[PDB]
Length: 99
Length: 99
Ligand SMILES: CC[C@H](C)CN(C[C@@H](O)[C@H](Cc1ccccc1)NC(=O)c1cccc(O)c1)S(=O)(=O)c1ccc2ncsc2c1
Image 1 (cartoon, rainbow over the protein chains, first blue to last red):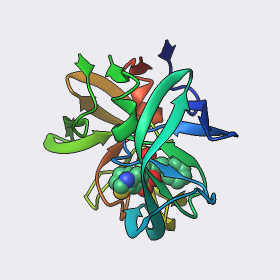
Image 2: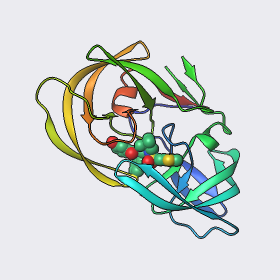
Image 3: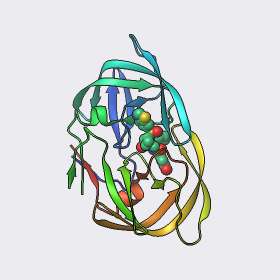
């Protein structure tokens, strides 16, 4: 599909049996999700943006479904105000910028 | 052009006869540039990102040529971690997400 940018590029994602709205974000290196208690091992990390840094938990090899497309990779979990699908997963679902 | 996302979508922009590198950032509502001088009146503004809120200077009706495509619109100047082109200008240059 094609998504114009008049509004925020929010789409439905699925991780386990939680469905969430998340930004398709070309400015995000990594995928950052709102606080959720995912199973398995993780590592602490700090990521920076406008306003400074937040602390996140890095979970690896998490399957995630984005608009019916299958992805699997690293997801950072922490106190972000919005769910952010970053480039690590955008490539997996075949996402490009075009103009 | 078509831009893939295995690397950061950094492009050369021209603003005030100056060449800068900026990130095409679909998760950003606004276009935010690192500290620089621009002519004319500005308004104090505050914006929020992943790490909290910052103060920026709001310049309106500023021409920027992004990867050869002309835009004229609002540019915020302040302590962003990197120059970002947000949706306000991405729409002007006809940028869409496709997968
Ligand atoms: C450095 C370039 C940018 C600012 C990085 N950010 C992505 C950017 O699209 C973020 C995404 C976002 C949206 C809404 C609330 C919080 C965050 N956008 C913004 O900061 C933003 C948003 C609205 C208006 C505005 O002027 C700026 S990010 O801070 O969210 C981010 C995301 C993923 C990531 N992975 C490693 S560092 C890192 C930082």
